[PDB]
Image 1 (spheres, helix red, strand yellow):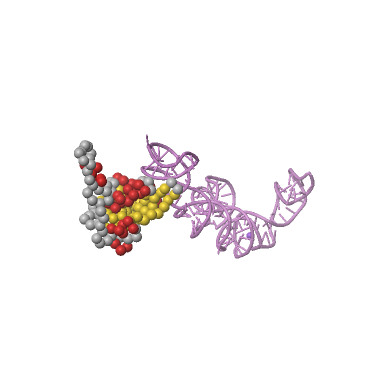
Image 2 (cartoon, rainbow, N blue to C red):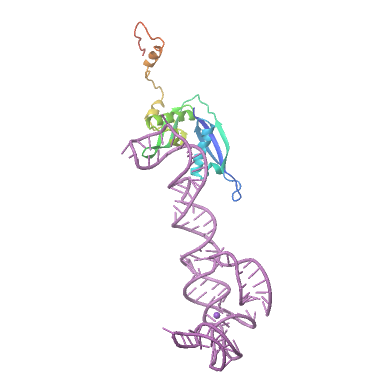
Length: 173
RNA sequence: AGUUCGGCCAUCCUACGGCGGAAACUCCUUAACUCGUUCCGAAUUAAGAAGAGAAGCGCCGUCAGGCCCCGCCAGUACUGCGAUCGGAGACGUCGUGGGAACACGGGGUGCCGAACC
Ligand SMILES: [K+]
């Protein structure tokens, strides 16, 4: 559901400063209306330009090619009930937006932090040798094999319409 | 440049060093008359022209105190509207608007209007 957007903005031009500077950002958001709001949240803190005093020049939407599985490293900050913290996370996904979906669900589940509690500092691709987290690194290898981690899930699902049967089914492994 | 009468009432004030005076303003000289000092010609009232740039006044100066403008401080402190956001609470968070002060660093240091020499 996440999407990559590039936003340009600038302070409204005046007599003291004709041709103000242009600032660009990369944003991940579910749509164009949330993305432009998040651009004004940062430009107000980092550059002290409220939304009343500036204008947005573009909301570029960028669609990425998948088809191969890469590593990503996300540097972010979030807020808990006792303060603010920094954190680095690693994930394997096919596009950057999909890697941000995975991050937001792990923050929501293990830290209970929602979307507006989180500021993304950095998102970059990480080559296989340079990985630093054990979970990701296991799969950055040649020849990884494991048996199915939950084959019971197949059997139960079929038993939701086939409510009564004549023998208890097996779980092939 | 100067004197009398004013407007706005320190970018004009206060302190200490300087520099100036043809004219002008001042300081200054006098106790007959006028009038005056809880005592005193100090002040003030009258009458004058020997002397002055020592003061006041105008100008210049000072890592000067004050005062005045700008930037920073800072989209920080605080706050209007909305929330079946978090927390035992005290309190905090997010969305959408408004937005300081102290401190700090650089600059500056009266102008306008009538009449006369
Ligand atoms: K003098």
